[PDB]
Image: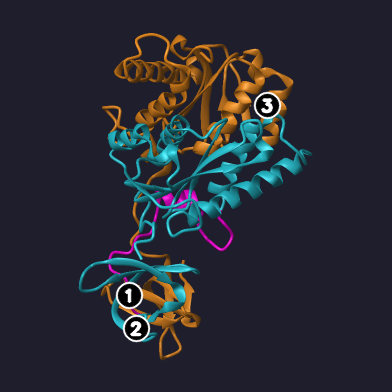
Chain colours: A cyan, B orange
Amino acid sequence: GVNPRGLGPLQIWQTDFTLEPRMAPRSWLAVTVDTASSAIVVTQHGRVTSVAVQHHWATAIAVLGRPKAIKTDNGSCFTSKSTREWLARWGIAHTTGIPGNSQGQAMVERANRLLKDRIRVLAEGDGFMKRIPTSKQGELLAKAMYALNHKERGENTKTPIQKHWRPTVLTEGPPVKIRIETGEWEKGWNVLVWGRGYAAVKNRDTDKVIWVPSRKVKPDI
Amino acid sequence: GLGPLQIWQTDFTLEPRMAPRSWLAVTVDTASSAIVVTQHGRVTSVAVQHHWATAIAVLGRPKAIKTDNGSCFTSKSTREWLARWGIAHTTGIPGNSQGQAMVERANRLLKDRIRVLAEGDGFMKRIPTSKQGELLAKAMYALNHKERGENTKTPIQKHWRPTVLTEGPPVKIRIETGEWEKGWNVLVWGRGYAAVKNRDTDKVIWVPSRKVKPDI
């Protein structure tokens, strides 16, 4: 249940590498998403390396501030003594899951899709149904980052950038009931975040926070 | 002229420590004092365009930008570029205090940071190319996320005015009398119910979503 999802900005980040053929020859995009505000940072790289990753996070930090922890996968660029020491110097905790849709890399997985679609739209919009000219990649990538952060993601009233600097973080949370394994509804929990997919619930007696499927929680009354 | 994203000052500045791409494009928001920098091989039109695209992805779209009268700012591409971005562009004589003094000071602050970081990492001369990108980002992080000295607010604080909201927007709830009473704020929505907190009694109750509405 300790899913990598922060309750507020700068608590938990998810970083990843995604290939975008449209941006070749340097088609590697390093992507990071603040699991709480959902804002994202992307940089272009010609190769998946520890050096690239370090350069990438330094950029994200410059943009979003210093996070408390970053979740990634077992990739060598993340587990290298070099990066491990880099994180340590920045005082940023690190956790590695596994390359996939495993609880700990899903949010950044979706961020890749979003980023990729935005790119395809700006690419075809400029007539580049194929590879984007090398000299127009930077700007186009920035245009994408801009759109994704400085413009609500539809269902949301507020934009990511809005959620990042001026977040809403409840101090207590209304009481709820969660459907325990037995399929029975249990009292004693309060919800702090209730998304379409997942809800964050804290235990009233242990102050433990866990994320559960939104349909396993209902108002307590 | 308080107000972020109102007026920006942009210029180039030479920094040998960043060679080959030793030409740094510099922009500073005249209200928040936030600074964005990108390195380039040569001062051109596409360069400023790349820089502004970047600076925008970082700080947002500006209303107007000021520069000197160098070719890269007064060319055809650049003017059309800004027009497409819908950004007002003014020029002036290089150094003109009117609208170049602040970015000029920005130049020096940037360079000082670069020196300190570079030397601090054992680079007394040209900083290795592979490490330039990160150092540049580290500089921006310091210049924008840390206080200068006099000012008690950091550029990021002036630019984004961060704060932590502890409740949703003000709402009104239909009571048993059919009336819509104000004084409540939405905490969380779910399962067709809205959890509202009274901003007077701090009382928190669950109320059917249908009996909830905004309150200006």
Identity of the residue drawn at 50% across and 14% down: B13
Identity of the residue drawn at 62% across and 13% down: B70
Q: Foreground mark, 2 or 3?
A: 3
Q: Which residue is mark 3?
A: A135
Q: Residues within 10 Å of mark 2 (few under 14, many from 20)?
A: some
Identity of the residue drawn at 51% across and 21% down: B99
Quarter of the image for residue A194 reads bottom left
The overriding secondary structure of the stretch rendered in magenta is: loop
Q: Which residue is mark 2?
A: A220
Residue B193 in the image: state x and y as whole percent.
Answer: 44, 80
Q: Say whether marks 2 and 1 touch (CB < 8 Å).
A: yes
Mark 3 or 1, nearer chain start: 3
Q: Residues within 10 Å of mark 3 (few under 14, many from 20)?
A: few
Alpha carbon separation for disc pair 3 and 1 = 52 Å
Question: Which chain does the residue under circle 2 lie in?
Answer: A
Alpha carbon separation for disc pair 2 and 1 = 8 Å
Residue A82 in the image: state x and y as whole percent.
Answer: 36, 31
Alpha carbon separation for disc pair 2 and 3 = 57 Å
Please give left or right for residue A199 compared with residue A30 in the image: left
Residue A140 in the image: state x and y as whole percent.
Answer: 65, 36
Quarter of the image for residue B2 reads top left
Identity of the residue drawn at 35% across and 13% down: B123
Q: Nearer the viewer, residue B88 or A190?
A: A190
Q: Which residues are magenta?
A: A152-177
**Residue A174 in magenta stretch:** yes
Q: Which residue is mark 1?
A: A174
Q: Nearer the viewer, residue A71 or B198?
A: A71
Q: Nearer the viewer, residue B40 or B185?
A: B40
Please give left or right for residue A87 compared with residue A23 in the image: left
Marks 2 & 1 on one chain: yes
